[PDB]
Length: 458
Ligand SMILES: O=P(O)(O)O[C@H]1O[C@H](CO)[C@@H](O)[C@H](O)[C@H]1O
Ligand SMILES: [Zn+2]
Image 1 (tube, rainbow, N blue to C red):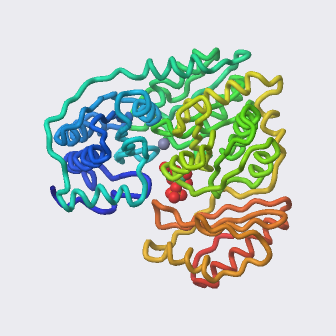
Image 2: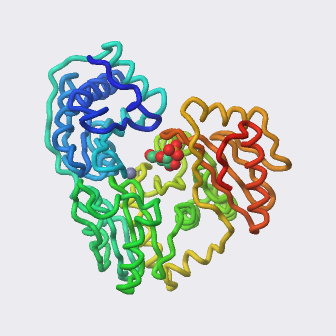
């Protein structure tokens, strides 16, 4: 084994720039490492999937070989969305799966999301593979590969369990990512008319990057929805584990709003059920979950960390501000933008109101988008520690499971470190503009007390 760069081994996945920090050799050894760990957990069967990035076809061969060279039985499911790979690792013989994807990033990025024996790896488990390659703590065997055509199985699974009450007109924007393989087809099969936008799978991303979290990547969907008098706009990120929602009047629906609608529907069918959300989500979620008799669980940001939490709590649903939505009710508990789109359409089809009025019916508060402060990699965790240790917030409920969050009577604010970039991530919400500004001023002062050079942009 060679000496791989440590930067590519991250908190919830492995990611690198192909030809640079991610090469054919890197992919092979990563496959060796994942195969050895899956075999240590008693799992020789590993599903393997890839997204529609230019480097997919080449690099996936190396991943497959590394797993085969452990003695693993590989199920090659070809080019599929991320959640279709997570589904493979739920319905096939083995409970391990590797997805070769670079998510929503520039054409040249690629990487790995890993499930081993039911568990999606995070933090120390990702380092554990890095360390296997360093130590040559690797299995050796003569494995096998079989091709598995899994997409029709998935498609059918969703179609059979969803029941739309009326037809709808839906603009689907796949941003040329791998969602194009199934999203337009399936939504139409549920009973919709589908206006496609950027639905051809093209790893050059010649339109807008498939990242529905940036509002400018929704400009075209919004214009198309209005132009065509459509009922709803939907947008998927590169690999299909995130969705973004636009109303019939062009309103962008923040994922924590989307969760409110899902939470209302799931809890109403399952009294007492647990519902998970990350620390960036509106507080309205607590009240709405509790009101319908559910149990609101606030947790850490990060898909792998949310999946783990759902297994521990038995939550029937989870959601993140980033747009990852995890259904266990009627499903398997992994994030899936395409399945979530199907669940949204189902609910919407049953309402006599247009999508604008269905979502406007949850009212509003004053809130910020995500704010980002670029710090250093040396200092980012230290600042958060310093805030958690020594900051003074005034009267409020202080939550520290991921950064610092303080819920005041009339609003809330959050500061956490990003697990992927040398940045501090903030969000604020409030009943009033004045209160928003009161909270923002508290956070500004507290950050300035740690380091009076920090560029607080509010
Ligand atoms: O970089 P961050 O802010 O730690 O984490 C971000 O990227 C992850 C990508 O998988 C998501 O799971 C998180 O929801 C998102 O906030
Ligand atoms: Zn994604």
